[PDB]
Amino acid sequence: TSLPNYLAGNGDLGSWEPTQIFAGEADIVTEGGAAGADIEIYQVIAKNAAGAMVPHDPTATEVPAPQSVAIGIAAQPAKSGQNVPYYIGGVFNHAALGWHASLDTLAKRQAVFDRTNIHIGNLY
Amino acid sequence: TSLPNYLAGNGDLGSWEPTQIFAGEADIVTEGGAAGADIEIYQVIAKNAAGAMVPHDPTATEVPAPQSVAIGIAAQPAKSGQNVPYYIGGVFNHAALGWHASLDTLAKRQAVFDRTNIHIGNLY
Amino acid sequence: AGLYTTYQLLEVQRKLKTLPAFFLQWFPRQINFQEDMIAFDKVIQDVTRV
Image 1 (tube, one colour):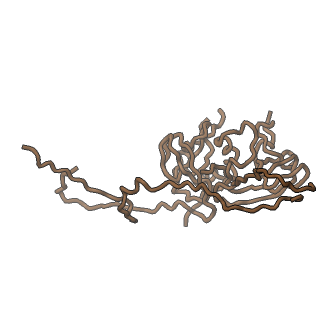
Image 2 (cartoon, chains in turn yellow, red, cyan):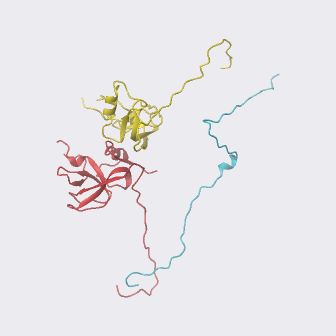
Image 3 (cartoon, rainbow over the protein chains, first blue to last red):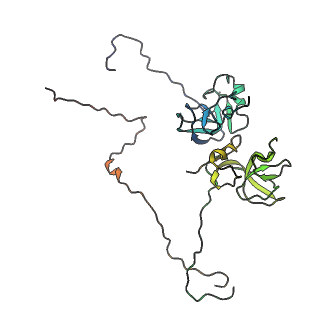
């Protein structure tokens, strides 16, 4: 942690690309709640039977279980037991969010939100 | 109702407490419809099989009956056969609203309005 | 009287409970900054060995 580096090398300081979360001009609406599992920023969120925020997981059961219906988008990261602030409404950039696997194509990723204030859109 | 009072005396004239209905900043949106039952102010409402507003009644049925899915919040009270103005969108303080029995905790009171334009949350 | 009694209002009474600044007396320096974070360097130099 205090040795300098002597051997010459290419100086790649870093790289950056904006995370454009919003893909529309609708109502942004938010509330935070207790988290039931570790949740990252702009992850897609569901709620377990206990009512805690849990990362969205389709196909979680032979009867679908409540973690399988997405309910919002995390606004800040939080470990279990903490409170997660999450978006309830708005138009969101398809690509910015944390979707779980097997929810690959935009066709599916919209199918997760075909009624609520959350709508998922392309950028241009 | 005729005479004054000449004798001394005290009187507790009354008390006033504000009722705060809104708990956030979604687009507040309203609609009007015929009532099917006696509805109180800010009572949570559903629509029965005949399309008339009826106070929300979860576990109405063995298939669930349409009274069981809440659809809005009464803006003014009404008797059966009268029109009820009610909210269909907005963020509402769960405490001010009239709720069914056994719909006690906020964790349950949110579950009634997840797939919806209304969202219900705590005041600070 | 009769219909409804006339009233004389006395001045309003307000139990305005503040919470006074006590601990902030030991935080006199104010820094308003737009950088992401504030940083300190702390140096311990024991020039007391034999």
